[PDB]
Amino acid sequence: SKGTTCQKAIVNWEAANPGKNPSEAEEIKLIFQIPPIEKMDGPVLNTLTKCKKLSLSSNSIDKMISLNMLRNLEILSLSRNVIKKISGLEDIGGTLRQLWLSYNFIEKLDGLNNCSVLQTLYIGNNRIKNWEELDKLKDLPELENVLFYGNPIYEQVKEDPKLIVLKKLPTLKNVDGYIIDDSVLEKVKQIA
Amino acid sequence: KQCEIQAEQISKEKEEAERELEAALPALRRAQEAVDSIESKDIVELKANKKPLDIIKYIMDAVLVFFKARLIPIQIEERVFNKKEGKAVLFLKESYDESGIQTLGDMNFMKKLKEFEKDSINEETIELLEPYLNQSEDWFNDTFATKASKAAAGILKWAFAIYEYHQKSKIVKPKRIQVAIAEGRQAIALKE
Image (cartoon, rainbow over all chains, first blue to last red; front, side, top):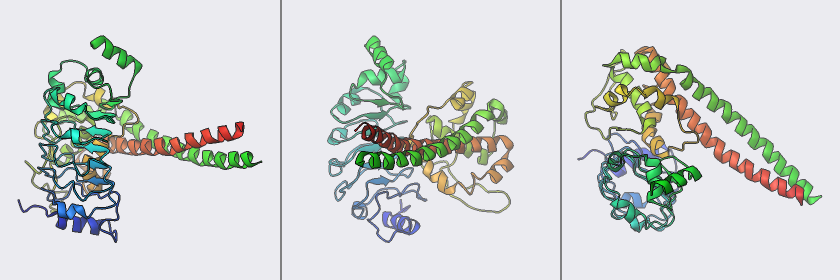
């Protein structure tokens, strides 16, 4: 609402980093801008050519747009935004390894399947209420690390989330900051 | 004679990586110890506080970050809070509304703090905490903490101590893995 321009924020961001190149940086820390970075402009972001990590955390981001013109993006982290739908991630889908998106308002996991090479998906204290989304998430062949503590589903579950998580997805190695255990797998076998 | 020179060179890389490992353990110990030495002493003086000030509330947030529970987002219910005598005006996400009323009344408050998972990467939280690290020197300085209250300072020593420990554990794993790999290459070169 005329709060933070991506160019205005990038201007301070590039000046604060004091880096000669506006698209040389692997880690483009645009986090916690003030007033907060509302909606991200794709033409501006396109610049970031060498950026492996793009931290736009803790701002007032409502939508995810302009995956296009992103080459080497490995760890996209848009946590504590106001984001509702995981969409417009087809052009980063080739590279994207980790989608850190905690404390959003992500109710549905519809559009996460485009992420083919996604290794680590942290979406904690989100709005995921049914395990229906987990079946859609199961398409991910390389998904190792998940974080689903604080979601509205794990509240209604009425059992150990660590155990109930591991049993839900066989692919997942780490679930809510745990490691794949022999005792946990046996407990998952006793549950199912 | 070739395999000897190889074993020596790698055995030098062992010693460097051991010293890095040795520097981090102390630095981890130093921090976690202060957290564990506080005990319920400060936790009791918070439970007594009941209606705390807008300075010590932020100090609870830094702790609430590590719990990963009901954390408030966005520039909503936020304003500006005066520091000491100097009429300074700053922009911050502001305390929880009702996250503390639920954290407080939980008797396990002590149990939740006293125990933390080791080798916790917490990239989700450190991204959310990044805003508070650049501002660290303004509010979260010890000399502004102890002034707000003695407990507060311990909790701001509590919150920071974990941030240090985490950073040390995040220097341990990589520089100790590169050690453990090198160590393996030397052992093979010695056998050869």
